[PDB]
Image: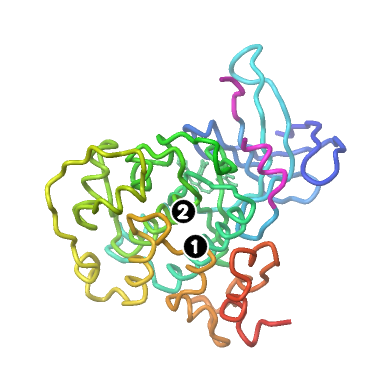
């Protein structure tokens, strides 16, 4: 029942005994294995991610500090299933749900996720992206499963930095990255010089999925993923193909008309949600809004209303405590982002 381990963790390099109990398996996958546990001293729930080390998550997790990113409490090396292999354990903050599971509850119940939650969850996702992109860090795996959620407080926390990397101009990066459904079209065209706007495309895919109740681009392969994008956005132009990958020149594809954005979504869909979505799911990577510009979109105006409350009656979580680092990409947007009632 009680497991005792020694571990340094974030902040100062000082290993200490951490005792936890009520260990339970959350899930298994590409990430490794994630367990739920309770810290004995405080009685706080935590998520322990055990990963086998062979063949940058730790490096990135020790530097990040944000309200919409799951924090690293502690980290330790241990034994595991495989003898003589080294396993890294990340003790992170526990959040009970995922955007995937919450969206799946509403879909199975023939409902669309309420707009108030679509606004709250997307705003906090873009806010977490504005923060990591201000350090040049691209997540490269934005999807509903990686967006942790606390249903009662409506707090969203971005997790799983196992695909994350600091993008530097001049250094190439792998094109086969991101879960296929949320993969930006530059990556499909084999671009190695892509930017952090691949996460904005992936966030646009998450937004569209919450408005439709099912993935907008459910491709069965890298090639079929592009067919799903073309069926909605229409055939990309030469300029768009050059913008996505400057070294691709061989795209022969039939002329498919774009599906108008008003027709993609159901008639009850708010126009501002559609308008925001059209500025994220753009072929040209530079034409996409930055995460900080997405936060300042008119679709999130209700969150900036002094009288906004969650359906349960609680206040919204913290949305306007922006740091200077977080506003770096566009300091003048602080006028829109921090409303009159939230300033000082
Ligand atoms: C294939 N799998 C099956 C399980 N599964 C799943 C089911 C329910 C929950 N509920 C939230 C529980 N808490 C939690 C989880 C992860 C972290 N984390 O930092 O990674 C933290 N801090 N907390 N999460 C997960 C989950 C999400 C992301 C990652 Cl990487 C790992 C897991 Cl198991 C999946 O999405 C897909």
Q: Position of residue 192 (x, y in %)?
A: 44, 37
Q: In the rendered image of this protein, does residue 128 appear above or below residue 294?
A: above
- Where does label 1 land, which residue? 290
Q: Which residue is mark 2?
A: 197
User: 315 or 141: nearer the eye?
Assistant: 141
Q: Over which residues does the magenta segment extend?
A: 51-64
Which residue does the image show at 65% across and 60% down from the upper left?
67
Q: Is residue 72 above or below residue 31?
A: below
Q: Determine the image quadrant of residue 285.
A: bottom left
Task: Quarter of the image for the C terminus: give it.
Answer: bottom right
**Badge 2 local density, few (<14 within 10 Å), some, or many (20+)?**
many
277 sits to left or right of 6 = left
**Quarter of the N terminus within the rendering:** top right
- Classify residue 260 as left or right of residue 98: left
Label 2 element class: helix
For the point 81% across and 46% down, which residue is it? 11
Q: Position of residue 178 (x, y in %)?
A: 43, 41
What percent of the width, then of the height, locates residue 343? 69, 82
């Amino acid at each position: 029942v009680t497991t005792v381990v020694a571990t340094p963790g974030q902040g100062p390099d000082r290993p200490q005994e951490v005792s936890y109990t009520d260990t339970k398996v959350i899930g298994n996958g590409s990430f490794g294995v994630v367990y739920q546990a309770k810290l004995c001293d405080s009685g706080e729930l935590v998520a322990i991610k055990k990963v086998l080390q062979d063949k940058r998550e730790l490096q990135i997790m020790r530097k990040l500090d944000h309200c919409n990113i799951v924090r690293l409490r502690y980290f330790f090396y241990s034994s595991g299933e495989k003898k003589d292999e080294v396993y890294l354990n990340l003790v992170l903050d526990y959040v009970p749900e995922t955007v995937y599971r919450v969206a799946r509850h509403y879909s199975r119940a023939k409902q669309t996720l309420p707009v108030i939650y679509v606004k709250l969850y997307m705003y906090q996702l873009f806010r977490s992206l504005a923060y990591i992109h201000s350090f040049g860090i691209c997540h490269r795996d934005i999807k509903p499963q990686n967006l942790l959620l606390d249903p009662d407080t409506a707090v969203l926390k971005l997790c799983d930095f196992g695909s994350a990397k600091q993008l530097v101009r001049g250094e190439p990066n792998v094109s086969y990255i991101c879960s296929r459904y949320y993969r930006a079209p530059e990556l499909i065209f084999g671009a190695t010089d892509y930017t952090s706007s691949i996460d904005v495309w992936s966030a646009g895919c998450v937004l569209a999925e919450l408005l439709l109740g099912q993935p907008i681009f459910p491709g069965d392969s890298g090639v079929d993923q592009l067919v799903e994008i073309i069926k909605v956005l229409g055939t990309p132009t030469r300029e768009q193909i050059r913008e996505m990958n400057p070294n691709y020149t061989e795209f022969k594809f039939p002329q498919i008309k774009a599906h108008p954005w008003t027709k993609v979504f159901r008639p009850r869909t708010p126009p501002e949600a559609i308008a925001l979505c059209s500025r994220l799911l753009e072929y040209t990577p530079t034409a996409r809004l930055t995460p900080l510009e997405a936060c300042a979109h008119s679709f999130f105006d209700e969150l900036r209303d002094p009288n906004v409350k969650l359906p349960n009656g609680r206040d919204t979580p913290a949305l306007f405590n922006f740091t200077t680092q977080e506003l770096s990409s566009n300091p003048p947007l602080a006028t829109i982002l921090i409303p009159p009632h939230a300033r000082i």
